[PDB]
Amino acid sequence: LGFLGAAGSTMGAASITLTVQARQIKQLQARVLAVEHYLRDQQLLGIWGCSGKLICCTNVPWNSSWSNKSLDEIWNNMTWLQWDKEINNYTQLIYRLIEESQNQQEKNEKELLELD
Amino acid sequence: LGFLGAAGSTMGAASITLTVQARQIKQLQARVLAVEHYLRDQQLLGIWGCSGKLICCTNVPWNSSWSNKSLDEIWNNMTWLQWDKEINNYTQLIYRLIEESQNQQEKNEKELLELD
Amino acid sequence: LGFLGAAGSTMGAASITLTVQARQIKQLQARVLAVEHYLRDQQLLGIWGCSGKLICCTNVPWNSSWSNKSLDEIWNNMTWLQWDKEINNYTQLIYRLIEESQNQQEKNEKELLELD
Amino acid sequence: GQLVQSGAELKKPGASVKISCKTSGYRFNFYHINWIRQTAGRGPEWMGWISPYSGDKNLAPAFQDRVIMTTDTEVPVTSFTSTGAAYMEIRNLKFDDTGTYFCAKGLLRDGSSTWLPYLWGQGTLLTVSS
Amino acid sequence: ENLWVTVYYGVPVWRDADTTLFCASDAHNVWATHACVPTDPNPQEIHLDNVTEKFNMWKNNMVEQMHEDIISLWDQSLKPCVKLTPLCVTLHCTNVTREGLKNCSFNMTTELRDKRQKVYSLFYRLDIVPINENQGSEYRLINCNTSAITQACPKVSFEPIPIHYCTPAGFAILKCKDEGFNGTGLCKNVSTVQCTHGIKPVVSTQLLLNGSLAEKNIIIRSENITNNAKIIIVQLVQPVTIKCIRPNNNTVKSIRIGPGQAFYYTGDIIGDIRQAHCNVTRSRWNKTLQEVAEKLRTYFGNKTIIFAQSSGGDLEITTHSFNCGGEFFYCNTSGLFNSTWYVNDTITLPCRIKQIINMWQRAGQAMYAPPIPGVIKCESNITGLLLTRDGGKDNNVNETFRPGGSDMRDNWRSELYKYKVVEIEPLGVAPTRCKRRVV
Amino acid sequence: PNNNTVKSIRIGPGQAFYYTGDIIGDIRQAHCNVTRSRWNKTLQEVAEKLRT
Ligand SMILES: *[C@@H]1O[C@H](CO)[C@@H](O[C@@H]2O[C@H](CO)[C@@H](O[C@@H]3O[C@H](CO[C@H]4O[C@H](CO[C@H]5O[C@H](CO)[C@@H](O)[C@H](O)[C@@H]5O)[C@@H](O)[C@H](O[C@H]5O[C@H](CO)[C@@H](O)[C@H](O)[C@@H]5O)[C@@H]4O)[C@@H](O)[C@H](O[C@H]4O[C@H](CO)[C@@H](O)[C@H](O)[C@@H]4O[C@H]4O[C@H](CO)[C@@H](O)[C@H](O)[C@@H]4O)[C@@H]3O)[C@H](O)[C@H]2NC(C)=O)[C@H](O)[C@H]1NC(C)=O
Ligand SMILES: *[C@@H]1O[C@H](CO)[C@@H](O[C@@H]2O[C@H](CO)[C@@H](O[C@@H]3O[C@H](CO[C@H]4O[C@H](CO[C@H]5O[C@H](CO)[C@@H](O)[C@H](O)[C@@H]5O)[C@@H](O)[C@H](O[C@H]5O[C@H](CO)[C@@H](O)[C@H](O)[C@@H]5O)[C@@H]4O)[C@@H](O)[C@H](O[C@H]4O[C@H](CO)[C@@H](O)[C@H](O)[C@@H]4O)[C@@H]3O)[C@H](O)[C@H]2NC(C)=O)[C@H](O)[C@H]1NC(C)=O
Ligand SMILES: *[C@@H]1O[C@H](CO)[C@@H](O[C@@H]2O[C@H](CO)[C@@H](O[C@@H]3O[C@H](CO[C@H]4O[C@H](CO)[C@@H](O)[C@H](O)[C@@H]4O)[C@@H](O)[C@H](O[C@H]4O[C@H](CO)[C@@H](O)[C@H](O)[C@@H]4O)[C@@H]3O)[C@H](O)[C@H]2NC(C)=O)[C@H](O)[C@H]1NC(C)=O
Ligand SMILES: *[C@@H]1O[C@H](CO)[C@@H](O[C@@H]2O[C@H](CO)[C@@H](O[C@@H]3O[C@H](CO)[C@@H](O)[C@H](O)[C@@H]3O)[C@H](O)[C@H]2NC(C)=O)[C@H](O)[C@H]1NC(C)=O
Ligand SMILES: *[C@@H]1O[C@H](CO)[C@@H](O[C@@H]2O[C@H](CO)[C@@H](O[C@@H]3O[C@H](CO)[C@@H](O)[C@H](O)[C@@H]3O)[C@H](O)[C@H]2NC(C)=O)[C@H](O)[C@H]1NC(C)=O
Ligand SMILES: *[C@@H]1O[C@H](CO)[C@@H](O[C@@H]2O[C@H](CO)[C@@H](O[C@@H]3O[C@H](CO)[C@@H](O)[C@H](O)[C@@H]3O)[C@H](O)[C@H]2NC(C)=O)[C@H](O)[C@H]1NC(C)=O
Ligand SMILES: *[C@@H]1O[C@H](CO[C@@H]2O[C@@H](C)[C@@H](O)[C@@H](O)[C@@H]2O)[C@@H](O[C@@H]2O[C@H](CO)[C@@H](O)[C@H](O)[C@H]2NC(C)=O)[C@H](O)[C@H]1NC(C)=O
Ligand SMILES: *[C@@H]1O[C@H](CO)[C@@H](O[C@@H]2O[C@H](CO)[C@@H](O)[C@H](O)[C@H]2NC(C)=O)[C@H](O)[C@H]1NC(C)=O
Ligand SMILES: *[C@@H]1O[C@H](CO)[C@@H](O[C@@H]2O[C@H](CO)[C@@H](O)[C@H](O)[C@H]2NC(C)=O)[C@H](O)[C@H]1NC(C)=O
Ligand SMILES: *[C@@H]1O[C@H](CO)[C@@H](O[C@@H]2O[C@H](CO)[C@@H](O)[C@H](O)[C@H]2NC(C)=O)[C@H](O)[C@H]1NC(C)=O
Ligand SMILES: *[C@@H]1O[C@H](CO)[C@@H](O)[C@H](O)[C@H]1NC(C)=O
Ligand SMILES: *[C@@H]1O[C@H](CO)[C@@H](O)[C@H](O)[C@H]1NC(C)=O
Ligand SMILES: *[C@@H]1O[C@H](CO)[C@@H](O)[C@H](O)[C@H]1NC(C)=O
Ligand SMILES: *[C@@H]1O[C@H](CO)[C@@H](O)[C@H](O)[C@H]1NC(C)=O
Ligand SMILES: *[C@@H]1O[C@H](CO)[C@@H](O)[C@H](O)[C@H]1NC(C)=O
Ligand SMILES: *[C@@H]1O[C@H](CO)[C@@H](O)[C@H](O)[C@H]1NC(C)=O
Ligand SMILES: *[C@@H]1O[C@H](CO)[C@@H](O)[C@H](O)[C@H]1NC(C)=O
Ligand SMILES: *[C@@H]1O[C@H](CO)[C@@H](O)[C@H](O)[C@H]1NC(C)=O
């Protein structure tokens, strides 16, 4: 299929290809920048508790104001490019909520570690 | 509380705030250096099997030679700054023991799985 | 032993030392290169679901065309240096198969949780 | 992997004999070198073995007072193969010591079977006569 | 049994690789060692049991990096320094009253643009070429028709300081420990270091000075011992002491060229004028030549070994160049290579000093070393030779060798022959019975 | 069309300057040729698109 060949496919179809895109003085600056972008996303996954996973479920409920579409209307009727545009203004809210949910989980894990 | 706000608090109190502190041409050198420090710490956690966790229990027994203090003398009576000075000469030894324990653990997990 | 001290040892014997090698203007270029080198392999482990592990079992079956050698012939009769040469032409093929298997596993675990 | 032994030789009783075992195609130091005797009246007998790496040797109780083993320093050919030779000496030969003598090398670099005589030389005859 | 792929990380394997190396040194030198990373107070070396590895000193790219760094450091040191372009002016010269020196006078610029001053100075004849008018009284500096000339800064030392070469993390340097090694073929004893031992930069054209010594026997190294085109590097077991002197007591004077600039020159010589020279003890050198001949006979069929002086070419080729006291010497080595060795006091080498040099033989570049005042003495060890075979002959009676080599890289090879750079690849895969459990 | 003869002089150490010292043969103005029939077809087609 190749890199980003899934971009025009439905979100459900695209989900099978995630590993394809997971891969990959001006020259020196470019090399540092490429590293920063890689790590930027990895830090977010670590913050969310999703590190090491391609697909990570969270405890944050879907908020219907972000989108009123049904799962079939999202997963089989849209591309990821279209989906990002539909919720482009809410992505920061979602990221913050995921972090807050992880913070509560870590507090609970701490108690469990002392108990057993 | 904010970044390093727990520094004067006891170690036990500080353990609550780890979530907060886990976060956060010359510019090029600054950017490279910031990356090296992030990865240095993550490399150790990955080797120890502690990646993705703020608090990670191990199978390494405490040597009374490293410290003769009781848990109460450590957790409720010390700052982390004071504690690091007490074990500054033993820290590298402890790190190697954690690494050996992780490698023995995974070897045993492999051998267990061979039976399935 | 020491860094790469196990290189001449058998593949089975060498496994006890994995942590030894897991750790560890021109000066700036050297520093950036070391980071890129480190991240290249960590990126593969993150995709494979093997992040945080020194030894990681997968769901990919061994294809006898890659090697027809018995486990004794590999683990008790080879160095890792010799082994890498034997499968040097198949290494990238194996890597892609691991990635495909992980993505299917991530999808299947998601579907299990959707049902439950 | 091949082993080559010294050709057959005729000895008088009480004479000493030295038998070489040239090796090629594999790393000499990586495997144990075994010696095995075969005589029609006794069947196969273990003469013990010598490590080319540590120099350690294990002679069977029957041969501890009569057999001496030594090896040459290996000379490399490739990074994974080398040449070299093992030698065995037998003191105070008897008519009972006649028959074929064999050189053999260990099966594995590790594991419980590491010293087993996987590869054998063609073997050569020793003869004793008055 | 059903085997499955298992991933291992931290696997002790490597592959040959070329990576940027950086300098390190022990805690103003021309090599800018202050810029280098401080060395570890207790350097580590790990012996690799059961490892045999192929080395090839003639394909080694550590040498190429060292050569580029040596040139680059040299050039950086000259960037702030005074240019002597105004000194390319007609010179009027007479004999000092030896032939090696001329007493020259010329009109040179001053701090003020509209003013000029007359300068008297002594120059070595090697730095002086006659003007095509051929009157015999008019001369110019030898490189004025080929390059700009830059004065070396008087504050900058040219003394060698050992430089350790280090590789980036994720890479390692393998070292051959065999008691004797040709720099090629398989090495039985291999160990790993993060950095090389310190290597002094040494510049020489025929003899290798202050290098490593062979542990037991003389080692002769060549890419192809039968090919006369190839340069033979000989490493000695024991050093032969060479001592050098410049008997002349130079008085150094300084005249301003212009604002922010100054020119240094010898204005006078105190006492008599004598030729610079270097001596090698005859008995020690003779023993060295015999031992080299004994080793050469093992490659050449026991033909009689003949040493001879270079057949010709530039002064930089035919003589032994070196930096002594900051002065650049060129010595006649025919005193060292005149012997014939059959199967069956001191040697004085005349020398010349040249202030204008072209060390890397680059067109368009030149440097003027300032004179160093007073009598200069040096001592160094001859630790190896650069020889070439005199080929084109079918004679079975004897064989002939001459000193020298085709490149500066041949010097770097004499220390780097034992080192190899490899990339460490921590990932690997292998079959196991182990299968991953799935939720 | 001109066959220039190029001569050089040294400005100073490390430098040289190149100039035309003479011209061999007649001295003529430089020029270019564009095929008329190809150019006419080319602009006619461009005009057809501009009209839209
Ligand atoms: C570089 O390359 C070389 C060559 O490849 C590598 O060397 C090879 O290394 C392997 C792994 O260590 C060795 O295999 C092991 O061999 C031993 C048997 O050897 C023993 O018997 C010798 C007998 O000779 C005399 O001494 C005995 C004493 O009782 C007398 O009875 C006899 O009459 C003789 O007098 C004895 O000499 C040996 O001791 C000496 O040599 C050993 C060599 O390794 C030294 O350590 C000793 O200090 C001493 O110098 C020795 O006793 C087998 O027993 C091993 O099998 C066990 O261990 C395996 C480890 O993987 C394991 O898998 C097996 O299951 C088995 O383990 C069992 O036994 C253990 C006993 O403690 C139990 O704890 C365990 O639970 C289980 O029950 C193993 O086969 C190769 O022989 C060696 N090859 C050569 C030619 O030497 C070298 O390692 C490489 N180097 C590096 C850095 O990689
Ligand atoms: C900087 O350093 C200082 C000094 O180390 C440190 O202050 C110590 O903080 C620890 C807690 O981290 C205190 O130990 C606990 O004290 C609990 C309360 O007992 C008394 O103090 C109460 C107020 O304490 C808080 O607020 C003050 C400022 O007001 C602040 O200094 C304290 O640190 C703390 O934040 C007070 O409300 C309480 O009230 C009693 O007395 C009044 C008098 O009028 C009366 O009216 C009330 O009815 C009541 O009788 C009392 O005065 C105590 O409960 C606690 O023990 C419980 O919690 C622990 C922890 O969960 C359990 O393990 C335990 O089983 C109990 O459940 C514990 O003893 C310590 O006393 C402080 N030391 C001093 C000298 O004040 C700061 O926190 C440090 N700052 C930072 C940022 O780290
Ligand atoms: C670019 O865009 C086009 C148009 O969107 C995409 O083409 C679509 O591709 C998808 C995925 O392959 C198709 O989805 C499947 O279509 C099948 C069509 O039926 C076939 O068989 C019938 C006869 O029985 C024929 O008449 C028909 O023409 C087809 O030959 C359905 O049968 C499939 O349903 C099955 O699978 C789905 C998904 O798992 C299940 O939910 C169903 O229950 C059932 O099991 C499925 O619907 C889609 O039809 C294609 N559209 C068209 C118009 O052809 C391209 O894929 C896209 N390219 C890329 C790279 O993304
Ligand atoms: C290279 O060799 C020459 C010759 O061995 C060395 O020169 C020698 O130097 C010594 C010390 O200066 C001289 O001794 C002096 O001799 C004069 C008379 O000639 C005397 O008047 C002094 O009082 C003193 O005794 C020695 O003569 C001189 N030899 C010659 C032939 O000139 C030179 O030093 C050597 N170079 C090196 C680097 O060793
Ligand atoms: C080379 O030439 C220089 C001069 O260009 C010589 O230096 C001069 O040496 C004399 C002594 O021979 C110095 O005079 C002495 O000074 C000391 C100072 O403590 C004093 O105690 C003595 O009584 C005497 O006055 C003179 O100052 C010095 N010149 C300079 C500029 O330093 C040098 O000696 C010559 N070298 C040789 C080997 O001849
Ligand atoms: C280093 O010192 C030696 C000894 O003083 C110098 O040797 C002389 O070298 C010249 C050539 O530069 C020789 O001249 C040649 O003679 C041969 C015949 O023998 C002739 O065929 C050549 O055309 C040329 O004329 C001279 O004979 C030789 N002297 C001796 C006694 O061997 C050598 O030149 C010095 N090297 C330098 C670079 O100054
Ligand atoms: C143990 O290995 C040897 C040699 O196999 C090669 O060398 C090993 C160290 C390792 O690098 C392997 O991957 C190499 O293939 C085996 O000896 C070989 O046996 C075969 C079959 O008889 C023979 O054709 C070869 O010539 C032998 N050696 C060589 C160098 O060719 C030996 O059998 C192995 N022992 C086992 C499996 O028990
Ligand atoms: C090493 O040197 C020998 C001698 O120069 C080379 O042998 C020559 O090889 C060529 C190949 O075409 C033959 O034509 C010549 O006749 C050979 N010369 C002699 C004297 O036999 C040899 O090739 C060199 N090796 C390498 C690797 O360059
Ligand atoms: C090379 O050797 C020759 C001798 O083979 C040297 O010439 C000799 O010079 C000495 C000293 O003047 C004389 O005593 C000998 O009689 C000379 N020999 C001959 C054959 O004439 C020559 O000087 C030597 N070259 C060097 C550089 O030392
Ligand atoms: C090395 O050997 C060559 C060949 O023998 C020598 O050249 C010869 O010199 C003798 C002197 O009597 C002549 O008769 C021969 O005719 C020469 N041969 C050729 C091919 O010209 C050479 O002189 C010897 N070198 C040394 C240092 O003795
Ligand atoms: C859902 O999102 C809207 C818009 O940000 C917000 O007003 C509302 O409170 C959210 N609902 C919940 C339950 O967080
Ligand atoms: C699916 O999304 C597209 C793009 O917004 C839209 O045109 C189409 O009508 C949608 N289908 C349904 C059934 O809503
Ligand atoms: C405690 O430390 C000492 C000194 O290093 C060491 O000798 C001893 O074995 C250690 N104890 C344990 C249980 O590791
Ligand atoms: C096994 O490997 C060979 C060589 O790559 C390949 O042709 C064959 O299809 C593979 N078998 C399977 C089942 O993948
Ligand atoms: C100086 O020496 C040169 C030769 O180097 C000679 O031509 C000139 O005439 C000499 N001058 C005197 C005054 O003798
Ligand atoms: C040095 O070698 C020459 C031959 O090259 C010989 O004549 C002389 O005697 C030797 N000197 C000594 C002191 O042995
Ligand atoms: C030269 O050799 C002598 C022999 O005593 C030794 O003392 C000295 O250190 C050596 N010089 C160098 C730079 O190695
Ligand atoms: C090109 O066009 C001009 C009119 O613009 C016309 O006169 C001329 O004949 C044309 N040339 C050709 C070759 O048709």
Image (cartoon, coloured by chain):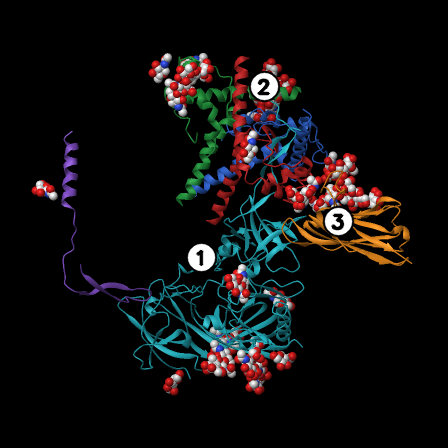
Chain colours: A green, B blue, C red, D orange, E cyan, F purple
> Which quadrant of the structure image shows residue C80?
top right
Q: Which residue is mark 1?
A: E72
> Which quadrant of the structure image shows residue C2?
top right
Q: Which residue is mark 2?
A: A108
Which mark, by number, is residue B13? none
**Mark 3 close to ligand 7, CB under 8 Å:** no
**Residue B71 placement (x, y as % from top left):** 68, 27
* Residue toward you, E100 or A42: A42
Residue F14 visible at all: yes
Asked if residue E297 is positioned above or below residue E345 in the image, the reply reads above
In this rendering, do the residues under marks 3 and 2 share a single chain? no
The residue under label 2 is which amino acid type? Answer: Asn
Q: Is residue E104 left or right of residue C20?
A: left
Q: Quadrant of the C terminus of chain C?
A: top right
The residue under label 1 is which amino acid type? Answer: Ser
**Residue A66 placement (x, y as % from top left):** 40, 16
**Residue E264 placement (x, y as % from top left):** 41, 69
Q: Which residue is mark 3?
A: D121
Asked if residue D115 is positioned above or below residue B67 in the image, the reply reads below
Q: CA distance from mark 3 to mark 2?
A: 69 Å
